[PDB]
Amino acid sequence: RPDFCLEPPYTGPCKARIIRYFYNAKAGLCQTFVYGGCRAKRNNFKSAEDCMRTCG
Amino acid sequence: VVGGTDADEGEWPWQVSLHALGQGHICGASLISPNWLVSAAHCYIDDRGFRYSDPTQWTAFLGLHDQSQRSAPGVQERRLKRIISHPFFNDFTFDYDIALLELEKPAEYSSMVRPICLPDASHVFPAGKAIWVTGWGHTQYGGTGALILQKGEIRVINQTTCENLLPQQITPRMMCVGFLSGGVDSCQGDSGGPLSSVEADGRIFQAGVVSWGDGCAQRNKPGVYTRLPLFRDWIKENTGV
Image (cartoon, one colour):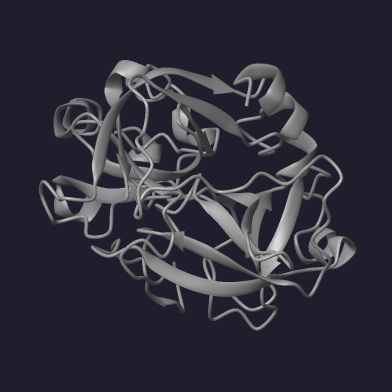
């Protein structure tokens, strides 16, 4: 439900390569994306579990 | 990085590949001595339940060339004793984005694993001066990393130009390096990596740490890195190097 769950995966201005999971709204499944390491947004977790437990 | 080409065995002996438990390669670092590195700061900031600051979660790769190559004759592997993010780093404005990583067991210099040279407090890298960026970062914004340490050539830029290309964002500890027409620039996964500069004497000196930038290789959006001089004494004061 969290509205931030429906926002697109935000990478960020920094340049780290941290694979993170985000919920794919029109796909019901959480997926992978790269987080720059800064300014993270709410729809970015560490495990598929964490992702699917709050955006299911 | 973007717009660059494959480097050669040992072309950048000071480059390093940093990995974190369950995540593979994350950032790059710079070998500044037998027991220390010089990376970013954001790379080691506890987030999403992972201790990105905890040294027990990191492995460093000296002399690395091919990421998919397991066990290599010229690649050293070491754990970290401790990380020292700058006491005035800012996870948001990106100021003081710099940190020191201490190796447990020392590095053992060789043809493919040599320490880069630190600019002395007052060194200057005049704008327009070509320098190099290296890393396994994404090869085009929004893509994937590279198996082989890529190399790219960019140049220093006027500070005001920098400040104004990225409105109300640049700080004295920062420095724009790249091109106005982009095409070449550091990208995700390159962070902490060292800007290598060939100096008039023949030796290469670290002139910056990959930090951030809006996008990658965009026109009017050159990479933003951490100036290395202002922290020379901070290094001396901490590492002891």
